[PDB]
Length: 207
Length: 207
Ligand SMILES: *[C@@H]1O[C@H](CO[C@@H]2O[C@@H](C)[C@@H](O)[C@@H](O)[C@@H]2O)[C@@H](O[C@@H]2O[C@H](CO)[C@@H](O[C@@H]3O[C@H](CO[C@H]4O[C@H](CO)[C@@H](O)[C@H](O)[C@@H]4O[C@@H]4O[C@H](CO)[C@@H](O)[C@H](O)[C@H]4NC(C)=O)[C@@H](O)[C@H](O[C@H]4O[C@H](CO)[C@@H](O)[C@H](O)[C@@H]4O[C@@H]4O[C@H](CO)[C@@H](O)[C@H](O)[C@H]4NC(C)=O)[C@@H]3O)[C@H](O)[C@H]2NC(C)=O)[C@H](O)[C@H]1NC(C)=O
Ligand SMILES: *[C@@H]1O[C@H](CO[C@@H]2O[C@@H](C)[C@@H](O)[C@@H](O)[C@@H]2O)[C@@H](O[C@@H]2O[C@H](CO)[C@@H](O[C@@H]3O[C@H](CO[C@H]4O[C@H](CO)[C@@H](O)[C@H](O)[C@@H]4O[C@@H]4O[C@H](CO)[C@@H](O)[C@H](O)[C@H]4NC(C)=O)[C@@H](O)[C@H](O[C@H]4O[C@H](CO)[C@@H](O)[C@H](O)[C@@H]4O[C@@H]4O[C@H](CO)[C@@H](O)[C@H](O)[C@H]4NC(C)=O)[C@@H]3O)[C@H](O)[C@H]2NC(C)=O)[C@H](O)[C@H]1NC(C)=O
Image (cartoon, rainbow over all chains, first blue to last red; front, side, top):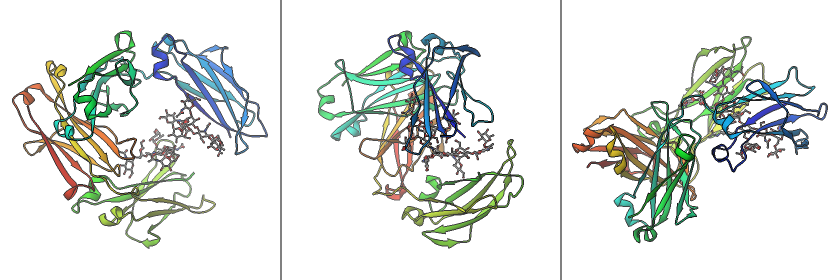
């Protein structure tokens, strides 16, 4: 029978009024026998009717994939409302229901700390600039780097890790040329999270 | 079902001759009728006979979970030999085979750097001591912390993250009392990896 995956908005999308947060309900393994798929959507159990279902697309394994997209109000997602996708197909014993929402719990403001390169690293070509983001809840967060207003490419961020107290931490590492650092350029760690003032903070770093 | 999952040894176990590395073959979704399951094990195609089947554990959905544990030679796992778990059950059309081995490729030695607390953090009760381990391959690694020979409790380690060059990094974070740090105790990050001399290195940290 067919399978359903329900996907949440991206963190940045819910934190910025300029962006468009969406919940996405994907049905795969729809057969040729029974290709009609119905979607019902509920917000905290109350049916809504504004979702955009794009038309089915047969995959290269001869099953159909159909997608339905519900736009969410920023504040609804953040006030913790619950999004239910109900999928009907005549090849199911019963309809499939998936639910999604923000992780439950009291939001906690991340602490952001920049850490310079270890002395040992300075006799390398590259140097790692570190951004420690700890104490946050839920785990949804965006981290970015920049210097003089231009975004930086060459950085990697760990997944959020669960701390003993139920909050999360992560580290972001920006790899720069030793020279750029040692001439004293300003590097900035950006953090976006619901529990920050204006959903944004920036922490700077130089020699 | 039934379905089979095949798990590698723990990093520490393969890196120390004193410990016992095992590969673990887990079967799930075996029913109450025929919970009979046979395991065959091969090391680079050659059958071995020293695996131990631990007793069934039914779970709250009334399917059985059945586990078989094969202890492996340290050097075999590290020389990249291939471990095949073959599962037989009357509810299979044909037997299930899973294979596992160490990630292929030249091992690379982790670079290990301890980073003191951010200035900002020093006006907290707790302080974060950081251990940056980068440049290592494969991703199998153990990190531990200590002071005066005694292990530390209160630390968390990120999973390995893939860098742009195909190697991995992680961070380990040790949370201590400000006092302990500011009295100038020595804190040590231990790292165990196959590409280190004696599979082990240690880096120290103090005020
Ligand atoms: C037939 O074909 C279709 C279509 O595939 C296409 O055509 C075929 C022929 C090939 O050529 C393919 O290469 C080609 O792509 C097959 O459809 C696939 O079906 C599988 C399941 O059989 C689905 O698996 C799920 O994948 C999601 C992740 O999917 C996202 O990321 C993928 C990239 O890695 C990407 O391909 C997907 O499109 C999708 O992308 C996301 O889309 C949203 C909305 O569009 C977007 O906003 C996101 O940004 C975007 N993300 C990215 C990364 O770009 C994965 O999460 C699922 O995992 C859950 O379920 C598994 C059980 O199946 C389980 O093992 C996992 O652990 C996991 O379990 C979940 O865990 C969470 C906790 O983490 C828990 O809370 C959840 O409750 C739990 N989930 C459930 C429901 O229990 C899952 O693996 C493929 O996505 C799907 N592909 C597409 C494109 O639809 C089909 O399988 C083929 N049929 C047969 C019979 O072979
Ligand atoms: C009935 O219940 C049982 C019991 O489950 C328990 O009870 C139920 C009711 C629920 O409450 C559960 O939440 C609860 O756990 C169900 O049994 C489960 O069955 C599923 C599916 O059959 C299994 O899924 C797989 O799990 C592995 C992860 O396994 C480790 O981590 C789990 C926690 O996340 C943990 O539960 C496991 O026990 C295990 O933990 C490790 O165990 C070994 C054992 O020796 C130990 O040495 C380790 O140290 C230990 N680690 C630690 C510290 O925890 C998951 O990885 C699998 O996903 C792979 O395959 C998917 C395809 O199915 C794919 O989507 C994933 O991405 C992933 O595959 C990756 O990519 C490809 C495939 O695309 C693959 O080839 C790659 O190898 C792989 N890459 C890498 C590197 O990851 C998979 O999801 C559950 O583990 C299992 N739970 C238990 C405890 O047995 C049962 O299904 C239920 N029956 C019914 C009614 O259906």
